[PDB]
Amino acid sequence: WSAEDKHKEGVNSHLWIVNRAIDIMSRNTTLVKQDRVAQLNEWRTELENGIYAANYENPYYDNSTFASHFYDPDNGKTYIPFAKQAKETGAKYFKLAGESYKNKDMKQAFFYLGLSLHYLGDVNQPMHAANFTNLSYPQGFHSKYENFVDTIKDNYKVTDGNGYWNWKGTNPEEWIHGAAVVAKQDYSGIVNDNTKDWFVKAAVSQEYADKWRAEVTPMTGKRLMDAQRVTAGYIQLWFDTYGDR
Ligand SMILES: CCCCC(=O)OC[C@H](COP(=S)([S-])OCC[N+](C)(C)C)OC(=O)CCCC
Ligand SMILES: [Zn+2]
Ligand SMILES: [Zn+2]
Ligand SMILES: [Zn+2]
Image 1: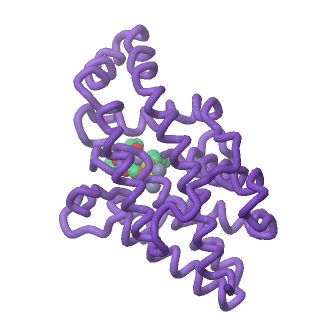
Image 2: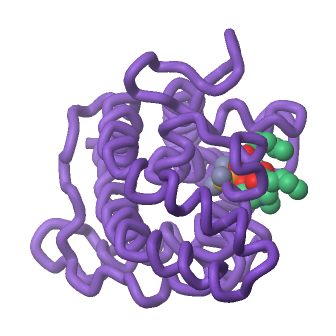
Image 3: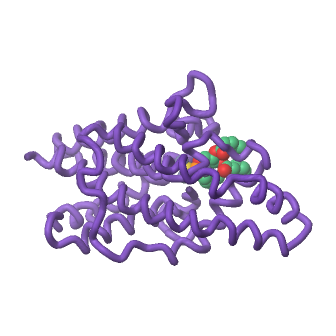
């Protein structure tokens, strides 16, 4: 997903997915300790910094190849042979965040949590779980899709407090893998001969540009809602793990 601006949801789907996940935690009145939501906002600057850094600097963006932002659950690999992938990279920062949290270094803890949230966010994007990059055919489709997503995401906010509490085990890796498994299933609903064709023709016909946008919207909405619920449960797991209990 996009992350064009460090502090604005308008062009940052990643931040939007997290803010909505936090809203799910606020809406929950039976399980979530609201003190946790208070902490996230208290260190919101470090959180958002982490969410944004993943796409603009090393080692997070792997020299502009973003190899660590992909993870195919079937073979457990990214699109580049022998490169680091999203599951191990996301888990890495989840743990680094927790250790800094236990040493009372909040700035460090939430920066790292932000990075981890970014990776978990990417595997909910079908293309990232199937190694379809911006250079994959049709080229340019990957980024134009993620840009289009920012214009319609607000129509798919989860308005209840039911996140996927303890969705997977206690190992962050299981959550990233589990999320990628679900996103890869919805891959075909976004990337297929039709969308490929219309996206190519869209170049010379405004008529087609709208055609693929419409075709990918339903599945996009479904992917966005899941991402919010899984992220909410992921954040809750982090706090239960390092929250000193
Ligand atoms: C100018 C063309 C770059 C387009 C692009 O979508 O780059 C970032 C994504 C993956 O990262 P995510 S978190 S979904 O980043 C989307 C936002 N931007 C483009 C601003 C980093 O990586 C690629 O598809 C690999 C090939 C690069 C030419
Ligand atoms: Zn992304
Ligand atoms: Zn992408
Ligand atoms: Zn990314």
